[PDB]
Image (tube, rainbow, N blue to C red):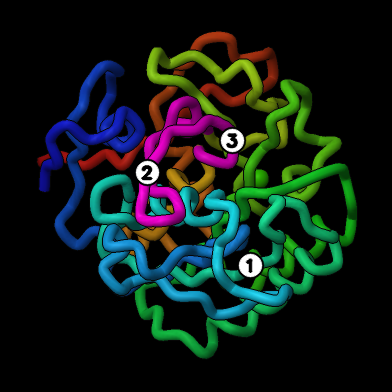
Amino acid sequence: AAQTNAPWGLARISSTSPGTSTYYYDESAGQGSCVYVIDTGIEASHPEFEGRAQMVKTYYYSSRDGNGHGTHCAGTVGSRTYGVAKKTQLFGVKVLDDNGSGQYSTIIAGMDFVASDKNNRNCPKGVVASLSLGGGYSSSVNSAAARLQSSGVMVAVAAGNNNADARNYSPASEPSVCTVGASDRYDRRSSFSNYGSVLDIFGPGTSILSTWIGGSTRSISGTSMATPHVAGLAAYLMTLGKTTAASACRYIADTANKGDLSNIPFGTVNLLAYNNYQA
Ligand SMILES: [Ca+2]
C-alpha cells in the first residue's frame, strides 16, 4: 500500500532517506492488534478513526478528550490518514485530565488497568501501549511500566522534552520498556528531545500532523508525538508476525536506520524507526 502526500512522519518510517511524502506499508496495516493510548482520552467520534477508537476507562468526570493531546497521539497510531497502523484497534485510557496533567497514582493505576483489561479485548495479533506522558523520576511509575511490559504488552514511552538525559524521568528511565526520542524531517535530533543510554529508538517528533478534537487536525511537536509512531509500528510489525511484545522494542532497534541522525549525543543510540517495508 502507498499513501501519497502523507505527512513526513509516516513517510520517514517507511524510507531509508528523508524528504519523501509517500508512506509505504503492508496492507494488513495493524488489523488484529490493539494499541492502548494512555493519555487525555480519544475523540472516538472522529471520522478519521472509522469506529476503531473507543474509550475504555476514565479516572475523571468524563472520558471525552477535552484537550486534544490524546486524540493527537491516537491519530498517529491508527488514523486513516495520519496513522501508522490504519486498521488497528485504539483503546483510550484517560489518566490525564483536560489540562494534560495527572497524578502518578492515577497514571500508575491506568497501567495496571491495561495489564488486566487486555484480557477483556480481542487482540490475537498483540497488544501495544503508547505512554505519551511522563514526569520526574519515580520507581513506582517505572515498576508500573515494567509490570505492563511483563504482562505481555509492548510499552512505548516518551523520552521527554527536557533536552537532558532521560534517566531522571519516569517511565522513561525504565529499561524494560521502549523509550522513544524525537527527530525532525531533516534527520536531526529534535532540540527538545531527551537522550541518554536508556533511549532505545528515535521517531518522527517535530511538526507531526495528526487529528485534533472537534473533528479537526493540527501539527505539533514533542517526544509525545514520536512515541505513537513506534507504538503504531510495533502493532504493525505484530500482525505481520515479525515480532512479539517482549521483543518488539529489540526488533525495532535491530531493523532501524543506523547512523542517519545528526546531533546525537555520545552514548545515545543513532536509531530511527523504520518499517523495512519493500513494496
Ligand atoms: Ca529499554
| Type of the residue with mark 3 | Thr
Q: Which residue is mark 3?
A: 223
Left or right relative to 85: residue 113: right
| Residue 255 visible in the displayed image | no
On the image, which quarter does residue 30 sit in? bottom left
Residue bounds of the magenta highlight: 202-225
Label 3 environment density (alpha carbons within 10 Å; few <14, some 14–19, many ≥20): many
Using the numbered discs, state the Cα–Cα distance from disc 2 to disc 1 in whole angstroms.
Answer: 20 Å
Q: Give the residue displayed 31% in from the left and 42% down from the top.
A: 275
Q: Nearer the viewer, residue 131 or 14?
A: 131
- Per the image, label 2 sits on a secondary structure element best described as strand
Q: Give the residue displayed 31% in from the left and 45% down from the top.
A: 82
Q: Give the residue displayed 73% in from the left and 44% down from the top.
A: 172
Q: Which residue is mark 1?
A: 94
Residue 158 position in % (x across, y down): 63, 42
Residue 26 position in % (x across, y down): 18, 52
| Residue 7 visible in the displayed image | yes
| Type of the residue with mark 2 | Thr
Q: Give the residue displayed 42% in from the left and 16% down from the top.
A: 187
